[PDB]
Every structure is written in C-alpha cells, then in structure tokens.
Image (cartoon, coloured by chain):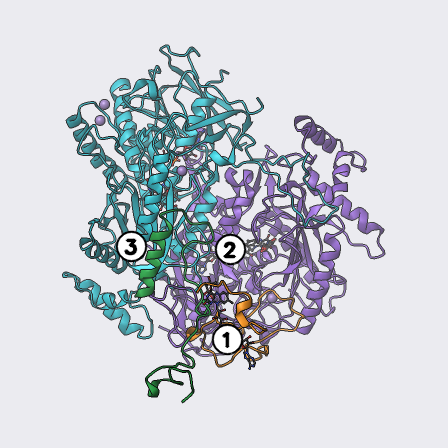
Chain colours: A cyan, B purple, C orange, D green
Amino acid sequence: PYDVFIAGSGPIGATFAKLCVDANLRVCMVEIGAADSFTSKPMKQFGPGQVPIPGYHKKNEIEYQKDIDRFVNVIKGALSTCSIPTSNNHIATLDPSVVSNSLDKPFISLGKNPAQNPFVNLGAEAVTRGVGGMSTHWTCATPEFFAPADFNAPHRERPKLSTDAAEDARIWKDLYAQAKEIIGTSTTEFDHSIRHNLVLRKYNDIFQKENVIREFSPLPLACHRLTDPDYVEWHATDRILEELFTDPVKRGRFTLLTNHRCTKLVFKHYRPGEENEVDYALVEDLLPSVKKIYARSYVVACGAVATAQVLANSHIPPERDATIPTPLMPMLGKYITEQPMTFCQVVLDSSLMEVVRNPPWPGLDWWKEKVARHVEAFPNDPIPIPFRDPEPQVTIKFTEEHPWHVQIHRDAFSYGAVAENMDTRVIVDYRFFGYTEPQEANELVFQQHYRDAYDMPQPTFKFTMSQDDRARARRMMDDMCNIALKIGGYLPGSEPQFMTPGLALHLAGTTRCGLDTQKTVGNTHCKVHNFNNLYVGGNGVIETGFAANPTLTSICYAIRASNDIIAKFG
Amino acid sequence: PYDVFIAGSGPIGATFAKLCVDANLRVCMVEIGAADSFTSKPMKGDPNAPRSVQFGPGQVPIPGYHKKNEIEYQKDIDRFVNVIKGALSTCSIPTSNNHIATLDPSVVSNSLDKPFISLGKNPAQNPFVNLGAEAVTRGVGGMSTHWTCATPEFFAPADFNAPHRERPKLSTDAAEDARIWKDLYAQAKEIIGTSTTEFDHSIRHNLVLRKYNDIFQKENVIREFSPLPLACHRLTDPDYVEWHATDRILEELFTDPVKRGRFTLLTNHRCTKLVFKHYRPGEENEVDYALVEDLLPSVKKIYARSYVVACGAVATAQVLANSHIPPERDATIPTPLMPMLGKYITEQPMTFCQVVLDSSLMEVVRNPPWPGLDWWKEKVARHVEAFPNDPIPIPFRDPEPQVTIKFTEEHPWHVQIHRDAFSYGAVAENMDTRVIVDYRFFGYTEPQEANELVFQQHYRDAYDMPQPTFKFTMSQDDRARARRMMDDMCNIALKIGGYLPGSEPQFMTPGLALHLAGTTRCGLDTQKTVGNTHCKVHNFNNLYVGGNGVIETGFAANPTLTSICYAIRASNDIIAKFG
Amino acid sequence: IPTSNNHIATLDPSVVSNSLDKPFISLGKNPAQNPFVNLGAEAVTRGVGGMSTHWTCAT
Amino acid sequence: ARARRMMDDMCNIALKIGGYLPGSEPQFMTPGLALHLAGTTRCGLDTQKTVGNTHCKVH
Ligand SMILES: *Cc1cc2c(cc1C)Nc1c([nH]c(=O)[nH]c1=O)N2C[C@H](O)[C@H](O)[C@H](O)COP(=O)(O)OP(=O)(O)OC[C@H]1O[C@@H](n2cnc3c(N)ncnc32)[C@H](O)[C@@H]1O
Ligand SMILES: *Cc1cc2c(cc1C)Nc1c([nH]c(=O)[nH]c1=O)N2C[C@H](O)[C@H](O)[C@H](O)COP(=O)(O)OP(=O)(O)OC[C@H]1O[C@@H](n2cnc3c(N)ncnc32)[C@H](O)[C@@H]1O
Ligand SMILES: *Cc1cc2c(cc1C)Nc1c([nH]c(=O)[nH]c1=O)N2C[C@H](O)[C@H](O)[C@H](O)COP(=O)(O)OP(=O)(O)OC[C@H]1O[C@@H](n2cnc3c(N)ncnc32)[C@H](O)[C@@H]1O
Ligand SMILES: OC[C@H]1O[C@@H](O)[C@H](O)[C@@H](F)[C@@H]1O
Ligand SMILES: OC[C@H]1O[C@@H](O)[C@H](O)[C@@H](F)[C@@H]1O
Ligand SMILES: OC[C@H]1O[C@@H](O)[C@H](O)[C@@H](F)[C@@H]1O
Ligand SMILES: [Mn+2]
Ligand SMILES: [Mn+2]
Ligand SMILES: [Mn+2]
Ligand SMILES: [Mn+2]
C-alpha cells in the first residue's frame, strides 16, 4: 500500500505530493483529466537527458507572450461550467416543419441541471480538469490574507489556526514564507515596466493628497522575468512537481495516474459520529476499468466543488430533485463563500503621455532611455511607451476600512471583444473583489438523480449574499469608479459593471477547516472529523469570508496537512 | 553532418522525417513553435515499458497529438472552438484609423493625421484583395493538432486533356499518371490513417446519409452521398474517437531507439532563411546551410546534404522569399532566383449554413424503413426507455453525421454535411444539438498569374519574418461557379431541415478554408512552376518544398492527403539521390 | 455624415461591390467632413413646430 | 478637464440610490447628441466678434 493517496493534481495536490515524497513516503496521485501542458528539465528540450514535466503554465508558450490577447481563448476552452439551469425558451422564427420544443415537451438537454434555481446560482462557477488544475491558466496573483490587530475583531480574512494569538501569527508568518517559496511569489518582476511604474507611482502621488490616503503596491505574482526581459515564466504545478520527475529517487516514490477518476472513497462503516477510516479509494480509468487503491492516508484535493463532490459521492456505500445526504460529514457544503466582482477598463489620460516623456520621480534613467529610444525610432507614434512594455501589476491591500481586494492590471481573461480601435499600451483593467460572510444556509449540494459528464453527482448551488455583503458591494463599485477615473476614462464596452456570480472562481468553504468542530468539516490540519486518515485540500478548506486571491493561503493549509500526515504516518 | 534538414513539423514535414529516417538517413527538423500537445507511448526496449502508465517511466511523450482527443472535448465538443481560435494567427490584417466617437475626451486618441501604430497590422495590405481569414498555426504538428481530419482524394476526369482537373498531373502519360496516383494515395491514407467507416453506427449519420440517397436517387439529376473519409478511429469505448495528427507520423522516431538516434527535433527554432552557394538567377545552385534561431531564453548554421521547406503554404514561400536577401516603404522582396514564388495562388470560396432536422424525421428515427437496422432500433429503444419524456428519440452522445458528395465536374465543388468543431457564431442556446446539421460547400478558384502572395521588405510579423501581403481576385468563371454552389447548398439543405436562426446561408470570409495552395507550385511546366513533380526547386540540386503550396491546380476538396502524396514522392527522390 | 469605403468581406462574389479605387457614391454623405472634428450626432427636424414636436420640454 | 469631473460626479450621484442597469453603464455620448449647438449666429455687445447685436439684428 502506498503511504498517501491524493485525488487531484492541481497545485494543492502537488504540494501534498512534493512534501510527502521529500519525507520518503510513497505517493499515488489520480488526476481525472489529461497531462496537456509540459515543459522539460534535465535529470538530476524534449530530446536526450531531459525529462517532460506536466502542469506547465500554458501562457509560457511564446505565441501568448507575443499575442497575449489570444490567451482568452485558452482560458475559455479550459473552463467547464458547474451548474447550468434548464430553460424552455420559445424560438419564434424556426422553420415551422423542424423539430421544436413546446410548453409541455421541453428539450431534455445533456449537461443542464434541472434542479438549479437560477436566482441562487453561482452561474459562472467553473472547473478545469487536467494535470495542474487551474494553475495551467491562472493569473498567478498571490497576496496574503488580512489579519486584524485585534485577534477578536468582528472580521478577518486570515483564518485562525490556534486560540493563542501570538502562536497563530508566528505559524502563519512562516507558512506564508514557505508557500511563497513553493509557488515562487515575487513583487519585483514588473519593476522595469513603464506602464507599471506610471500607474503605481501616479496613484500613490494622487492618493497622498486625497483626504483619505490609499496605498498602492505591486501585486505579488508567482512568476519570474526571463533573461530576455520580453518574456516571463508564469509559475504553475510543474514548479511544485519538478523534482518528482527530475530526481530518480523521488520519481521512484511517485505515481501519477492521469485520465483517472476518483469516484469515491469507501469507508470502514457508515455510522455518523463514530471514529472511522477510509478503507480504499475507488478509481476508474476513463480511457479504453474500476481499481481499488489502498493507502495508509488519503487526501482529496480536487478543488472546491469537486472535493465536496467526491466526499458526497462517498456517502453512498458500494424527489427527482433529492440531494445526497451527508451525515457522516454534516457540514459538507455548508457556509460556502464566493467573491462579488466589479470590473471596468480605462484608456489612460492623454496628459499622462507627457509624464511618460518627463517623469518627475528619481532613479528612472532606465525609463527615460527606453522612451527616448522608442520616440526616436517611431516619431509618429502618438504613444511614447515602448511596444512591448509590460502591463501594470498593481494592488491595494485589503483593509477593514476598504474591505475589498483591488487589482489594477491587465489580465489575460478578457470579458468581451478586444477593442479593435484602441492601442493596448494605454488600456488599464480594474477588478475589485468583495467577500461574502459565511452563512450556514449558503450551500453546495449534490444531486442523487442527475450526474455531470464524468458521471459524478451534479452540483447545485443555493447562494444568497447577506445585507451587509450587498452594502459592501455598493461601496466597492463606488470605490472602483472613483479610483479608475483618476488616471483615465472608461473604454466603451468595459464601463463599470458587476460580473456574473462565481466568475472569480474563488469559491471557498465547501470543506471548511477550523477550530470549531461542530461547524467545520475538518480540523486546522485539514483532517476530516472522525476519520483518522482522511484529509482535504484547496480553497474549500478556507472558513472565513475573504476578498483576496486564495491559492497561497490554500497552499499554507496543504503544508500543515502534509506535516500532520508525515507526523502520523511516517 | 545531417542527411536532411526539414523546416517545419506539421504532417508534411513529419512525412519527410518518417520516410527519410526509415531509409536510414539522419534528419534534423526545426519548428518555430513549441511542442504543446502530447500523447505517451511505451518506449521500445525500455525495462519499464510493459507495466508503464502514460507519462510515467518508461513511456515517451510524443508531440503533435490532436488536441481534440482530450476527453474534456469528446464530452463538451462545442468548447473546442476556443482551441481553434487560440491556435490561429491571422496572416495579413490591414491598418485602419476609425474614429471612436464616445471616448472620454480626456483620453489618449487617434486623429486623422496621427493614427495609432499597431505592430503586426500590415500597412501594405489592400483589404479588397485580401485573404483576410488566412491564418497559420505555429506548434509541433502545425495545424494537424486541431484539423477536422477530412481526407478525400482529388478528382481526375476521364479525359486526360479535360480543361479542368483537381488532381495535378505527375506524368504526361495518362496511364503512368494514374498508376503513380493510385500508389501514392494508398500510401498517404495509411500514413494519416484514413477511414470511411468510423460513423457507421451513428443514427444521425445514417439518417442523413440514407435519407439523402433515397431523395436524390429518385431525382432526374442523381447526386451520390457518401461517408466523408476521415483520418481517425473510433475507440473500443465507442463514445470516443482518436483523431489522427502528426503524433501518428512521428511516433516511431520517438519510440524506437534506433530511429530516435537518427532524428533531432529542435522546437522554438525558427528557420530564418536558407543561404545559397550564390545569388545569380537562372544558374545551377545549391543550399549552403540553413540559418536557424533559437527563440527561447543563439544564431546557428545547420548543414545538411538536402533541405526541405515544409512550413505551410504561406510560411514556406516566406522562408524562400527571405532567403533572397544574402547575408517604397511598401516595397516587396523580389524573388528572381525562384520567379514563380507566390504566383498563381488559389483559395476556396466557402458557403455555410446550419439546419434543424424536420420533425417528420423523428418518426423515421423511431421506425426506420431500411431493412436490417437492428442496431439502430436497439439504441433508440434504450434511449426512449431511459428518457420517455424526451421529444428527440436520438440517443444522447450519438455521433454527428459525417457525409460528403464527391466533387464532379457537373457540380464542381466539395460538399461536407456534418458537424464541425469550428463553430462560426454563438452556439445555439435553445436548440438541442442532436437535431442540428452543418453544411460547408467549398469551391475552387482558377490558378492565375496575377494572383499572388508577396513579402514586404520593411514590415515584419511577430517572429521577425517578412510580412505576407495578398493580391487575390477570383475570376468571372470562379464567381459563376460560387453562385451555383450557394444555390446547390440551399436546395440540398432544405431537403431535410430548415435553417437555424443565426446560421442562414452565407459566404464566409476569404481565406477561412485555410486551403491556400499554389504558393510554391510544382508540376511539369517548368516555366510556370517553382518545383518539378518531385518538388525539387528549379536550379537547386538539394532544395525541396512541401505542403499545400506545391499543389498547382484549382481544387475544392481538402488538400492534406494530396499534399502528403507529394511529400512521399519528394522523400523518395531525396532517398534515391542522397540515401 | 462622413464618407466611408469599408470592405464587406462576406458579399456573394458575383454581386455589385465597392473597391479600393471605386467606392459607392452615397448621396447625402459629406466628403469634406473630417470624422475626428465632427458633431456626428448633430441633427435637424423639419416640420411645423421644428423640434418642439418631440422635445423633452426642460426649460 | 470639466468633462472628467462631470463623469465622476455622475457616478458618485447615481450610486447613492441605485446600481447601474446592464447596458446603460456610465458613458459619454456621441458629440452633437444634445442638439444644443449654439453660437452659429452669435449675438452680443462685441460687434467685431458677433453676427448680430443684443437685439439679434445682423450687423
Ligand atoms: C482559471 C483561473 C483561475 C485562477 C485565476 C484566473 C483564472 C482564469 N487567477 C488566480 C487564481 N487564484 C489565485 O489565487 N490567483 C490568481 O491570480 N485562480 C484560481 C487558482 O487557479 C485556484 O485557486 C487553484 O488552482 C486551486 O488549486 P487546487 O485546490 O489544486 O484545485 P484545482 O482546481 O486547480 O485542481 C484540482 C484538480 O483535481 C481534479 N479532479 C477533480 N475531480 C476529480 C476526481 N473526481 N478525481 C481525480 N481528480 C479530480 C481536477 O481535474 C483538477 O486538476
Ligand atoms: C486549422 C484548421 C486546419 C484544417 C482543418 C480545420 C482547421 C480549423 N480541417 C481540415 C484541413 N485539412 C484537410 O485536408 N482536411 C480537413 O479536415 N485543415 C488544414 C490542414 O491542417 C493543413 O492542410 C495541414 O496541417 C498542412 O500540413 P503542413 O503543410 O505540414 O503545414 P502546417 O501549417 O500544418 O505545419 C507547418 C509548420 O511549419 C512551421 N513553421 C512555419 N514557419 C516556420 C519557420 N520559419 N521555421 C520553422 N518552422 C516553421 C509551423 O509553425 C507549423 O507547425
Ligand atoms: C429633438 C429634441 C430636441 C430637444 C430635446 C429632446 C429632443 C430629442 N429636449 C429639449 C430641447 N430643448 C430644450 O431647451 N429642452 C428640452 O428638454 N430640445 C431642443 C429644442 O427642441 C430646440 O432647441 C428648439 O426646438 C429650437 O427652436 P427653433 O430655434 O425654433 O428651431 P427648430 O429647429 O425647432 O425649428 C427650426 C425650423 O426651421 C425650419 N427650416 C430649416 N431650414 C429651413 C429653410 N431653409 N426654409 C424654411 N424653413 C426652414 C425647420 O424645418 C424647422 O421646423
Ligand atoms: O477573471 C480573472 C480573475 O480571476 C480570478 O480567479 C483571479 O484570482 C484574478 F487574479 C483574475 O483577474
Ligand atoms: O473552417 C472549418 C473547415 O475548414 C477546412 O480547413 C476543413 O477542410 C473543413 F473540413 C472544415 O469543415
Ligand atoms: O437626448 C435627450 C436629451 O437631449 C436634449 O436635446 C434635451 O435638452 C435633453 F433634455 C434630453 O434629455
Ligand atoms: Mn457572489
Ligand atoms: Mn504548521
Ligand atoms: Mn501541525
Ligand atoms: Mn477566395
């Protein structure tokens, strides 16, 4: 038997694999999707003594470094919508002899969820299936979560790991330091971008003179600029898995089964509230069947929706709208949280081009030389910013006084048609993410009689944000308009707007882990209550309402859980 | 050093690689793009192989795999349109200076006399003579990693001196030409893995094929409907298909250690230009070396006994144009060493529509009239039992139709009646996908000298190669055929269904077929060709071309299979001369 | 209303078309108007009452 | 400069009582849409810079 079985090969599952292998444990990881993105590294380019490493970021391919607007297509092709409501719309202009729906015989459409109420849905919530999970397309933003000065403040982003405030703080500090190294967070990789510096420095100058000061800083990113500074390597699961492929000793302790579905775990017994154990994982090989995989410990790291889906499916030992009850894990799927998001784009003020030509800040000879050079080579370009200058990567850290997360940047995930007519150097994006309070009645439940395309129980969302959440969302939209208009004016088609619920993909709380046993699925080590050898990972473990991007904080938890596993099962 | 240098790793370059390595020659292939789509196969002779798991020890990754083979896309095929749009880089986009009236008046703006300057728009391009949807894919396997896999033969008329033919002449003797093509086509179908039977137990395919033959067998002009030949095979789990791509061609160059030893594939390596022994027109000449650039974080000379440019129809001409510069702002690169380079280009006008199947055909699905269709009745019975309330009795996941009408000179176009991963508008949110059927009719254009691809001296693409510009105007005869084709499509479509809102009969943008041909055209008439019928470039003993750019005729059918035939023919010349 | 000469890529190839050098002549467009210095939505109403037969009546 | 201030004021004021209706988010309209074109026959005290006097008699 393996020492550790892991379902899922995203960055969290990879963290478990890496840490467990480094501690001399034998690990078997199942991934339901395909290894579809690779780099290569030499053994301790895809020819001789080099080894192929999957879970590489798709954006690292030179074609997307050159024509970055093409990458929206990658992301749209990677995302599979979780819950799509049925509908029965009349199509008036059909040819009258063709197949048609009617009031009494609607179409029955493969893939839709008849149980979903569209008014309580997270309609843009989605999943990516493949080695690396969502990390093969993500934006790589890795902020820390906010912790208030007072450990008993009414709200915090950063969960509590201890009732002892000073220990909690020291533990998080080092965890965040470790998770930064695992994923390779940096704040300096745009420090020689004109656009980045223009936006950062102008905003700080403006907000120093405003009646309420706001601090702008570089968005921390999991990436590194390459020796040819036109290119950036964005980090993904390949960085975490690397030595499991390139070190022959580690490679010998790691098995990765791709196109394998973890269908469910089978338990010693099905009695709620008594000590229990996983007996085996039931796994199906999806290519052209069923395997029991035995290990001493089991980790479900399938992302926020699918981790709960696996655990719900496991309640079934081996009215049409009935859901699977989950009394062995009563808090499964409860208290779920997602982030409201507002968006707009602006075109920079024409007066800022004078700033580009004559910047007032010291230490900027590098910028002066890039502008002078471009100006001399393209005297008729109305924009003096060099052609390939990187986009801005600016944030304002969450505070309780302005309790949302701000990104002022350019993202590969566009939301409508490129502006054919505007030059891309002068466009800036704003995404502002809010938080939702965890509430028991906000839920992810799984259908007994409808299944997804991979024959797993269909997820259904029952999400309604609170009055306080709505009041903050109004303030956030007001903040975005005010901030955006300081440096530019709205680009047509990207005026200030809310996006579809779920579109942030930051769903959390579906397998919530914390100190309060009766309201969580697992403890602070992510061990599921009453199971001696079952652990969860991913954003689903995060029990607080937060606004910042969660993956770094999720990796902290993966570290913790791996060390518990090592402690117990090494 | 190397016996053969190959620029390009699409299915044509791969064909040269496979055949040459099979003949014990040492091959170096450069590919400007990345290996980005893989499968894994056991490595022959590796102690791990018998028990191995995909992408484990001792399997080897094989690039150029079809992206549509991921189960994600076999289950959600409408998502694949995004893969296709992600893979296509448009060749020539005209500049424009449109006024945006609703900009905030404080922001950066274009003006009449100070337009924005965009990298990679082409100021030299006249939009009215463009192939504005012509595009390329840079990656291992080229476009074969997303293609639709249709592999028909080209039409050869009964009379060898008929005015028009799809299939080019390889000999002046009619009988030798026919024998040559018969052997090449057999070999090309085995290389790519063509089959006509992979949809034979789809209700939708069978419905569409049988109905149309029943209708047109009765009409006073008979039209014959047949399965579209497809480079694919259905898997032992019939819910999946393995679509074929360059991985099938290269497989043994990665799984066989003896072959792997003779093959080197350098990815993110641009062939910038070939450098010639000399630069005098009309004189015997040869390639000295290939100038290659590693584009990853440099400039290297690669020597071989023979050189193959298989970079697709546009890029092959681009590499050869740029090789004219040894080591008025709208001036193009003259190409006097290869005077027919980029002349006589052809492309396929295309009409498109979709229909919804007639309600009356659902009764045919429940009670097919044709004898011996027990398999169909069984599938339908299973579905109606599981989903008695479903108005559509076709089973979920029944495969799409895959039907064609072979080109004939009486109706001189290529028909596909199918469902294609390349959707052109928004998916139909309200209509069930089981009852939708697509129609793509492709015409041909006559080769004319004045139709050309040229390359800009002062403008470059994103990979620092000379910018392509098209000067393309179809002929009067090409236009009259296009109208007849549109008319035929409307007539044929409406026999089994009605147009789906949003996909009513329409022409598509010039270039969308991506069947550009004739840019390095090869044939018997030396004076009007870039290469001979072995695709050896005139006046160079050691330079060959491949791809759809070699095809010298006006054709309507999908060209890949015929391009493979030329690759075999050319490889054999290489092997006989240099191996 | 400024003149324009935009290419329509998807016309049926047998139909009447503009070209680079032979644009349509569209009566009532203004060849002298620079679009970037226009008041493009400026308009008149001809009829008894002029604009007062549709205006919002804010005074 | 005044138009940017005005856009900001509009966003601030609108959000005090409601939220933007999809499709009618804050935007500038095409110049001339107000139909409040003026000064084409300007009347005033300064004879050298007007068309008419303060009684609108043409000079
Ligand atoms: C798509 C996306 C995602 C993110 C960004 C932008 C875009 C468009 N931006 C972003 C994000 N997060 C950040 O913190 N900062 C950024 O700037 N994105 C989200 C981020 O990508 C996720 O938070 C992260 O991957 C979460 O990692 P994880 O917990 O490992 O989960 P994944 O979803 O990545 O991978 C899970 C994995 O398990 C597989 N699976 C699912 N079900 C099964 C079963 N039954 N058996 C076996 N395997 C299963 C999935 O296929 C998947 O690979
Ligand atoms: C995209 C597309 C393509 C086709 C269909 C559908 C779609 C959406 N469907 C289809 C086609 N063909 C048919 O016969 N039947 C169908 O059902 N499609 C076209 C087909 O895909 C092409 O005909 C075929 O690949 C051509 O093969 P090729 O001649 O080998 O050319 P490629 O373009 O595939 O690959 C060339 C290759 O060379 C590289 N390159 C370009 N420039 C350079 C330089 N300078 N140095 C090195 N390498 C270079 C490319 O990047 C590319 O990989
Ligand atoms: C169309 C409209 C206009 C107004 C608002 C809403 C809408 C959509 N709302 C509005 C406006 N004005 C306000 O102060 N507040 C409101 O809430 N609108 C504009 C207002 O409607 C005009 O300012 C007003 O009519 C102007 O009055 P006018 O100076 O009398 O000019 P008109 O354009 O109304 O009438 C001129 C008139 O003369 C005719 N004409 C033009 N050329 C000739 C020649 N050569 N020969 C003879 N007659 C001529 C016209 O045809 C017209 O009827
Ligand atoms: O929609 C794109 C956004 O998606 C979110 O998942 C990311 O965390 C942001 F960084 C990103 O801007
Ligand atoms: O545009 C998609 C079409 O493009 C062409 O490249 C293919 O040959 C067709 F089979 C396909 O239907
Ligand atoms: O566009 C309608 C607007 O146009 C103007 O002509 C009027 O003065 C405004 F009151 C009215 O709301
Ligand atoms: Mn929400
Ligand atoms: Mn710890
Ligand atoms: Mn611990
Ligand atoms: Mn054409």
Horizontal and vertical percent for residue B443? 66, 62
Reading the image, the residue beneath label 3 is A392
Please name the residue shown 50% across and 78% down the image.
Answer: B282
A521 lies left or right of B433: left
Residue behind mark 1? C2
Which one is nearer the viewer's eye here, A263 or B109? B109
Q: Which is closer to the viewer, label 3 or label 2?
A: 3
Q: Secondary structure at mark 1?
A: loop
Task: Give the chain of mark 1.
Answer: C
Q: Is residue B471 visible?
A: no
Helix, strand or loop under label 2: helix
Three-letter amino acid code at the position of disc 1:
Pro
Asked which quadrant contains residue B401, the reply is top right
Q: Position of residue A197 (x, y in %)?
A: 23, 57
Please tell me how crowded label 1 is: few (under 14), some (14-19), or many (20+) other residues with Cα within 10 Å.
some
Which image quarter holds the N terminus of chain B? bottom left
Nearest the viewer among B259 and A293 is A293
- Is the CB of the residue bearing disc 2 within 8 angstroms of ligand 2? no
Residue at 14 percent across and 61 percent down: it is A362
Marks 2 and 1, how far apart in space? 56 Å
What x and y, as percent, mark residue A507?
38, 35
The residue under the point 33% across, 56% down is D9
Q: Do dots 2 and 1 share one subunit?
A: no
Mark 1 → mark 3, Cα distance in angstroms: 37 Å
Instruction: Give the number of the disc on residue A400.
Output: none
Closest to the observer, A566 or A305? A305
